[PDB]
Image (cartoon, rainbow, N blue to C red):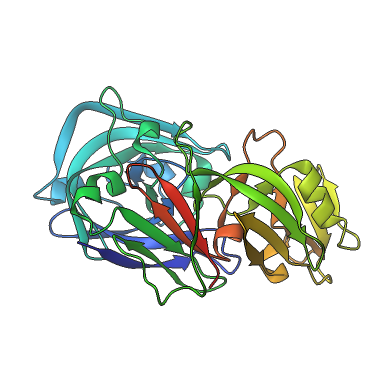
Length: 330
C-alpha cells in the first residue's frame, strides 16, 4: 500500500502545515499537524474542555462505529515551545491520503494549552517520530507510520513542504519526479526517539563552506531552524542591522533587508535555503522589525532542522530496520 496527501501552510508565513486525515466510520476529517518531532496522534474532540475549543474541528468518537475506548489509557504531552495537551485514548480507523490503519491509537484531548486553542486551523497532531516517545500510559502506543509499515510497499515516508505553497506527504514510496538530482542518505540515531542526524557543515550566502559536524533533528513540527550560537551569529552578521533581541526572543532584522541564503551539508551534498525562506515577517503588525527564521538552539539542548530547512528539500524518512534520512534538492 501507499498513501499521498497534500499538506498546506496554515498562514502566509508557513508557521505550520496541516494535512487532512480521516478518522472513524463514517469518516471524520480533521486537519492535523504532521510532526516528525513527536509520537502522539492527538485530536481536539467532543471531550475537550469547551472553553479550550475555538474554531477547531473535533473528533466525536460516539459517532464512529469503529471507535473503541482504550480502557484505562491516558496521555499527557509537553512540547518544546511550552505548549501541552492531555486526555484519554480511543482506537479507531485512520486514513491518510488513501492509506488506512485499523486500530490506531487516537488520543482524545480533554485539555489543551492556550497556544492550541488560539490556533483555529490545527485540529490536532500526528506524530511521526519513533514510537518510544509516545506518551500513552500504562501501555505505550505506536505511531501511524509504525502501524502502517508492514503494509507499505517500502517502509518510508517523505516530506515535501512548500514555501508559501502546498506540498506533499507520501507514505510507502519515493516520488522520483518530486526532486532534482540524487537523494543523499545519512545516518540516524534513534537513541533520543528523534530523526537525529549529523550535518556536515554550513555556508552563509556565497561564502565558503565550513566543514563542521552539527547534530540535530529533522522536525516538521518546528517552524524555524535552530542551530548553535556560533553558526547563527555568523549568519546574522551578514545582515545590516540584525541583532538578537531578548525582549522579542531571538534575532530580528530590518524588514527592508534582503537576506542571504543559508546552506547546510548532508554528507558531500548541499541544501540551499533561499534568503526569503528565512524572513518571518514583522514582529508585530505594522512593525519594520522582522523576525528571523534562523535562531539559536542554545538553551533548547538540541539543534532543530525545522520547516525553514526541510522545505528547501525533498526529505526521505527511511524507517527500515536501520533508519536513515535522505535529502534531495527540488
